[PDB]
Image 1 (cartoon, rainbow, N blue to C red):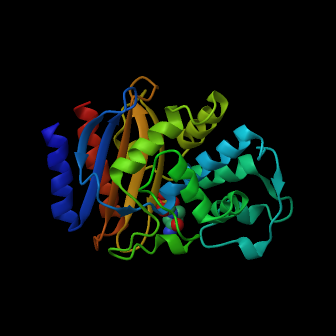
Image 2 (image 1 turned 30 degrees about the horizontal axis):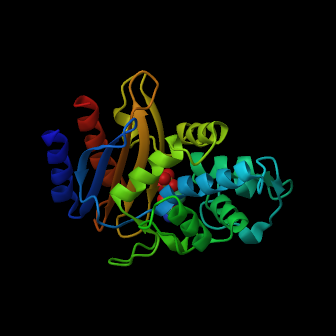
Length: 263
Ligand SMILES: *C(=O)N1C[C@H](NOS(=O)(=O)O)CC[C@H]1C(N)=O
């Protein structure tokens, strides 16, 4: 709808920064709306979804098992480690760590998961082999959140992420059991309250992953639809604004309110 685009433009005016936007039909993969679709934005914590997609790919092939227990130490703990800092004694399974990475955005969990697959480059190789020659992860947490302007490291485009997400959630890449583990983790997101979730009517489905970085970076990827069943993918990124966090949260909410009302 023109008026959802108008809200994206107004959000650009009021934040004083670039905003990338993609609305994708889950069934056919056709783009319903777009704004700056081929411009790069920092992925920030939204990459954790693509990371757990790579891990589930290894689980399918038998190179990884969801129950394998990983033991680490305080050393591996990096800033924002809400769950991993509580399991220094018993360790955590791959399944629990991916749950921590997506539902709580645990940073140490992400670094541990990156180690099991062979580092950021090997995640990029994973995305490359499924048809994403645009998205790239280059650094570990928390360095990947610097969001230096014009730096292409740890970036995606609204169109590339939205298509890759669609393949991960509904494509032929993962098995049915693996596809549902990723969507279940995303549905259990507990850190994207004031974003798209704030504008959701009762009975709607949402499975999302949010993120923020430096230089006013904020973003969300989401699978949502009415009556508890997803039907579209929404990708929203922004960077460059000197806005406070609560301000950036407000615009993504108004973008959410618009596309829900003109669903
Ligand atoms: C993801 O971008 N991050 C991890 C954590 N918050 O995730 S959230 O903003 O989606 O809820 C801390 C902030 C950020 C980071 N600096 O890693």
